[PDB]
RNA sequence: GCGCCGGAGCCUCGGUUGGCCUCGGAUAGCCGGUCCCCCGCCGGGGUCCGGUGCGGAGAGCCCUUCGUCCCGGGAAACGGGGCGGCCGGAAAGGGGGCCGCCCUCUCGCCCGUCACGCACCGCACGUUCGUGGGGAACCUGGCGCUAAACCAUUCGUAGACGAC
RNA sequence: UUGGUAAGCAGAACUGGCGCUGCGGGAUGAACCGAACGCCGGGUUAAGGCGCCCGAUGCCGACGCUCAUCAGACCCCAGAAA
RNA sequence: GCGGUGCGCCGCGACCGGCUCCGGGACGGCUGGGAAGGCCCGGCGGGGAAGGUGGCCCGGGGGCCCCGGGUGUUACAGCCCG
């Protein structure tokens, strides 16, 4: 039932650490709990454990003996950023960031809009309630 | 101020330390549903721990000293009394603030919280064995296993019908948004830019 | 150390049809139906291939003590399949 | 021995004072892995006092500097000949490691030997460290990393930072 | 109209193994568990609000039964959430685990 | 502290209200004044400690200020009586405030609203 | 002379500043809809479709009070306030649902136009559940009621005295 | 180091201590460690800990070891062999 | 009006000095007169392997695409030493 396998050359999202909020590819597996690149945000090659990573289901065939040049070429050829934008999780990460950095005046306007939306609920859902009561009785 | 805390698959000491920390700061705690508490170790040691507790008795008069309580709520009250300084007045106030019962009888229709720190899959390994507390209570003398289990099924059948009626209200919630989508489309776009639907 | 993978494939016949749901399988055939739970060992089952021809079992990252319990469950499954297909006839005599 | 943090390399050379009898003492070089140059030179005087007739009062230290690795990206399979002291008697071992840097391999060696056999490094010497080809490796836990076509999941995903939320309603599934 | 004060709880006093110090008070605000997160309330005033039997006068109003004890938040305590404070008069042992007000009008914004 | 921002009044008998800031006086006190219809705020002086600011900066470039008002004018003499000069000055300031706050949509509701906390709101977590 | 339901007043006391009213269990596997196909007096059994760092996200939902005049736009008139029946209701009984009506207007809420309020002029206990709990009398509508225990008198099946 | 086969036994060479000295830790404690004392306010530490009993590891700590059908929790100090 | 002493009660604000704790930024030397890092398979230019890469063969899962095992040193990719 495992869908996402740890495979050599798989794009993974870093959850936390120094490169917080960046994508990385599994270049080499040297130690049991230590992995071993992101050319888009200029991630320098270093070691990283398996705790602060969130893997995705995207791979491509390339040798691991190549340096940063062919990794950057494969990244720009595969164009991972458009698939990351099409991913539904990254479209709501920015929604959570906007909800965090929401202006209080904008929050007041959204609050009044949700008050009007709740009055629309109080009319329309009550009309569905009386319609369901007419269907039942 | 009232927190209802579930006790399914929760450890003794790990949950008890968190409850003893939160009660002394001041918060009404209702510990509910203590029947699936498991302790690490095999069935020999988890039985001989209680057997050593039975052997630690009073020789002159056993009707004055320790009492070997059979109820799991009273066992939890015993270990909370052992952890807390119950001689102090703040401990006596924590006894009034704390509320412990077995099963779930009068406010059964409430949502309850789960402490993840005392969880079995979090703390213990899945290869470890365990022993049940209600089975040991029924073997030592607690007679209300068949009384509680038949009353537990009565609230599960009521929650089966009510959640199905709660599911029926959820179809009416999404279908009402489809009918009135002409006028709320301006109200939809102002929430999608702020990021509430997505 | 923890061995990463030790697979053991089972070539079940066509007459033995199974349908797993979690760690609970059902076995049918010419005669007899037997069921057994497999929640305690916490392993991974995989019924692969078109028309369900073979079964696969996994034990990811287990040591020498935990990998020893994997092969015996395959023997119990083969004994269950033998009991469904052929059966068990035990003959025995009395001594006085 | 205080294994404070990672290890550092020090190319230490030293000799004795110029005598009126002989022109110069024979110079020697030692690559000491130590936390700092003070204990690097201390272990240098330790091994020199064990091997040759030389004392720290009648002697001198020529150079003690750090040189870095010329290939940090390339993987190297090291093999360390362990000389240690047991609680009853003295014995020797040999153990391989897989790490990029020599300092990282030596740093992992102290924690690994202290976990296995309770290595008190005050009287433990390292006589030889050398890189090994992939075919000449002995340990199966080292040789199992040599697999180009490998494809496997993770068995369990344990989560941390549970005291900061402190409350939850649904049960979180650890299957990821 | 509404609530104009956050929920702070008096936790205890600065104490060792056996001795205790009543002059330094320990406070804990609900919803913060970090030293970097409690940096916003450096200099906000605290007030233990209680009531009594006698009717004490109110500045700008009729006399009432309630009384206050003002204080000052100096700096934090511990790793995962605690803050230190010092009042004008020392609190008794009756005021253990009770609700206070956190006056935020000495602002730094 | 910039001219034109929205402030939360604290120390007055009107508290929790959202008042538009005008300018810095020569004495040192923050002269802050809301609409006479919306916020009901007169020409009142506050202090930089007692003022909590809110990041909403409207344009205040095209305004003017009279010179007859000073620090000695807004002094507590003794029975409070509203003079005829204060009403004319408040109307003259409100006539300059009026077109900008009418051009900004849904601003009069935020001005007439009052600040109040609820469950799960702590200002050190979220941002205004 | 005592009590069940609806005034002018008076002592004493403690925490408070909105509720979260709910299936189940898996954790090396689940959540939600159609369920075309069967068993079942209307629920499960599979089949399918989206999600899986969970949006059918408790890091989440709803209430939101500065007030009042007038003209408008969607909004809505089937709705809001209350009286009379019908059910649900006990592990430690809820002040819950629906329908007719004696009664009322298109006002509540979301945006535009205008006017007003002791605007108390720089320093604080404001903001609440409050027909809150306990004790005493003073008042007035509807409605019922005129009790028992102890000391002692006879008892030994009781028994130092009580006590039975 | 002597006398005893060994003791909380006796008798001797060097330093420090109770007696003449309390505080902090070691649960309670003549000798253990650190450090020695006028009365207060601020900042900061040794010895020591940071699941609760009381202030802190509630670090998004690492390496590996151990399942016991009588584990483990500290120098004095309160239990062990082949 | 100038100078000086003091308040019947409760509090707040401001500037100046001293003692502490913390945060945001900017500049410069050394190394092997730093190892290494990205840009023009950098061209010419000789050789070698395996965690065997294109391709070849063997066997089975899908109606023409993938798996495991050998052949191989560049080949429709890397790669270390001059």
Image (cartoon, coloured by chain):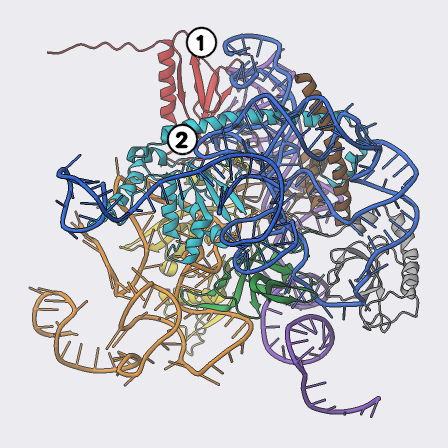
Chain colours: A brown, B cyan, C red, D yellow, E green, G blue, H orange, I purple
Does B58 sit left or right of A88 as displayed? Answer: left
- Say what secondary structure mark 2 lies in: helix
The image quadrant that residue A74 belongs to is top right
| Front-lying residue, D47 or C90 | C90
| Residue at 59%, 62% in the rendered image | E65
Which numbered disc, 1 or 2, marks the residue closer to the eye?
2
Q: Please say if the residues under marks 1 and 2 sit with CB atoms less than 8 Å apart.
A: no
The image quadrant that residue F82 belongs to is bottom right
Coordinates of residue A36 in the picture (x, y in percent): 57, 44
For label 2, the crowd category at 10 Å Cα-Cα, with few meaning under 14, some 14 to 19 and many 20 or more, is: some
Task: Check the image and report above or below for D28 versus B165.
Answer: below
Does E26 sit left or right of I64 as displayed? Answer: left
| Residue at 92%, 65% in the rendered image | F85
| Front-lying residue, F66 or D134 | F66
| Residue at 35%, 39% in the rendered image | B71
Does G161 sit left or right of D30 as displayed? Answer: left
The chain holding disc 2 is B
The chain holding disc 1 is C
Coordinates of residue D119 in the picture (x, y in percent): 37, 54
Coordinates of residue A27 in the picture (x, y in percent): 59, 40
What residue sits right under mark 2 in the picture? B148
| Front-lying residue, I58 or F36 | F36
| Residue at 46%, 49% in the rendered image | B97
For label 1, the crowd category at 10 Å Cα-Cα, with few meaning under 14, some 14 to 19 and many 20 or more, is: few
Q: Which mark is residue C15?
A: 1
Cα–Cα gap, marks 1 and 2: 46 Å
- Say what secondary structure mark 1 lies in: loop
The image quadrant that residue A76 belongs to is top right
Residue C40 in view in this figure:
no
């Amino acid at each position: 039932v495992f869908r996402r396998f740890v495979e050599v050359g798989r794009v993974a999202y870093v959850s936390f650490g120094p490169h917080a909020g960046k994508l990385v590819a599994i270049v080499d597996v040297i130690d049991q709990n230590r992995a071993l690149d992101g050319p888009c945000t200029r991630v320098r090659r270093q070691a990283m454990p398996f705790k602060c990573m969130q893997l995705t289901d995207f791979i491509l065939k390339f040798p691991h003996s190549a340096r940063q040049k062919y990794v950057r070429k494969a990244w720009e050829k595969a164009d991972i950023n458009t698939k990351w934008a099409a991913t539904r999780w990254a479209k709501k990460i920015e929604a959570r960031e906007r909800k965090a950095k929401m202006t209080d005046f904008d929050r007041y306007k959204v609050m009044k809009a949700k008050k009007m939306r709740n009055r629309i609920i109080k009319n329309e859902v009550k009309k569905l309630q009386r319609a369901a009561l007419l269907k039942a009785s | 101020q009232v927190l209802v805390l579930d006790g399914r698959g929760h450890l003794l000491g790990r949950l008890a330390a968190i409850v003893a920390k939160q009660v002394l700061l001041g918060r009404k705690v209702v510990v509910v549903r203590c029947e699936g508490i498991n302790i690490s170790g095999n069935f020999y040691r988890n039985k001989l721990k209680y057997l050593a507790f039975l052997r630690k008795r009073m020789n002159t008069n056993p009707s004055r000293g320790p009492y070997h309580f059979r109820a799991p709520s009273r066992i939890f009250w015993r270990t909370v009394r052992g952890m807390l300084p119950h001689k102090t007045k703040r401990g006596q106030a924590a006894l009034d603030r704390l509320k412990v019962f077995d099963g779930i009888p009068p406010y059964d229709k409430k949502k309850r919280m789960v402490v993840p720190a005392a969880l079995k899959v979090v703390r213990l390994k899945p290869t470890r064995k365990f022993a049940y507390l209600g089975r040991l209570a029924h073997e030592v003398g607690w007679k209300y296993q068949a009384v509680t289990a038949t009353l537990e099924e009565k609230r599960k059948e009521k929650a089966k019908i009510h959640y199905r009626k709660k599911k029926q209200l959820m179809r009416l919630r999404k279908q009402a948004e489809k009918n009135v989508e002409k006028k709320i489309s301006k109200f939809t776009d102002v929430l999608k830019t702020h990021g509430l639907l997505v | 150390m923890k061995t990463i993978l030790s697979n053991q494939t089972v070539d079940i016949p066509e007459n033995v049809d199974i349908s797993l749901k979690g760690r609970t399988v059902i076995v049918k055939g010419p005669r007899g139906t037997l069921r057994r739970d497999f929640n305690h060992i916490n392993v991974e089952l995989s019924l692969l291939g078109k028309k369900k021809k073979r079964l696969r079992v996994d034990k990811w990252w287990g040591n020498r003590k935990e990998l020893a319990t994997v092969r015996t469950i395959c023997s119990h499954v083969q004994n269950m399949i033998k009991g469904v297909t052929l059966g068990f006839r035990y003959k025995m005599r009395s001594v006085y | 021995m205080k294994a404070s943090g990672t290890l550092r390399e020090y190319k230490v050379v030293g000799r004795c004072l110029p005598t009126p009898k002989c022109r110069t003492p024979p110079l020697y070089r030692m690559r000491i892995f130590a936390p700092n140059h003070v204990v690097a030179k201390s272990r240098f005087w330790y091994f020199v006092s064990q091997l040759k007739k030389m004392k720290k009062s009648s002697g001198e230290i020529v150079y003690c500097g750090q040189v870095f690795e010329k290939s940090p990206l390339r993987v190297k399979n090291f093999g360390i000949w362990l000389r240690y002291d047991s609680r009853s008697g003295t014995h020797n071992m040999y153990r391989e490691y897989r790490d990029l840097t020599t300092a990282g391999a030596v740093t992992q060696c102290y924690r690994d030997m202290g976990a296995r056999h309770r290595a008190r490094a005050h009287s433990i010497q390292i006589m030889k460290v050398e890189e090994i080809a992939a075919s000449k490796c002995r340990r199966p836990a080292v040789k199992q990393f040599h697999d180009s076509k490998i494809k496997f999941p993770l068995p369990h995903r344990v989560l941390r930072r549970q005291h900061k939320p402190r409350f939850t309603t649904k049960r979180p599934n650890t299957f990821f | 109209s509404g609530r104009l004060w956050c929920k702070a709880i008096f936790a205890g006093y600065k104490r060792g193994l056996r001795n205790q110090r009543e002059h330094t008070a320990l406070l804990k605000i609900e919803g913060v568990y970090a030293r970097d997160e409690t940096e916003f309330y450096l200099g906000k005033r605290c007030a233990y609000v209680y009531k009594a039997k006698n009717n004490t006068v109110t500045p700008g109003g009729k006399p009432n039964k309630t009384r206050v004890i003002w204080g000052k938040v100096t700096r934090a305590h511990g790793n995962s959430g605690m803050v230190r404070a010092k009042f004008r008069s020392n609190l008794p042992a009756k005021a253990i685990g009770h609700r206070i007000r956190v006056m935020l009008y000495p602002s730094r914004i | 502290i910039t001219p034109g921002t929205i402030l939360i009044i604290l120390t007055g008998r009107h508290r929790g209200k959202r008042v538009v800031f005008l300018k810095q006086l020569s004495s040192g006190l923050l002269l802050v004044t809301g609409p006479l219809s919306l916020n009901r705020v007169p020409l009142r002086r506050t202090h930089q400690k007692f003022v909590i600011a809110t990041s909403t900066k409207i344009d205040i470039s095209g305004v003017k200020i009279p010179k007859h008002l000073t620090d000695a004018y807004f002094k507590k003499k003794k029975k409070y009586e509203i003079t005829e000069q204060r009403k004319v000055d408040q109307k003259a300031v409100d006539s300059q405030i009026l077109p900008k706050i009418k051009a900004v949509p849904q601003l009069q509701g935020y001005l007439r609203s009052v600040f109040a906390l609820t469950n799960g709101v702590y200002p050190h977590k979220l941002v205004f």
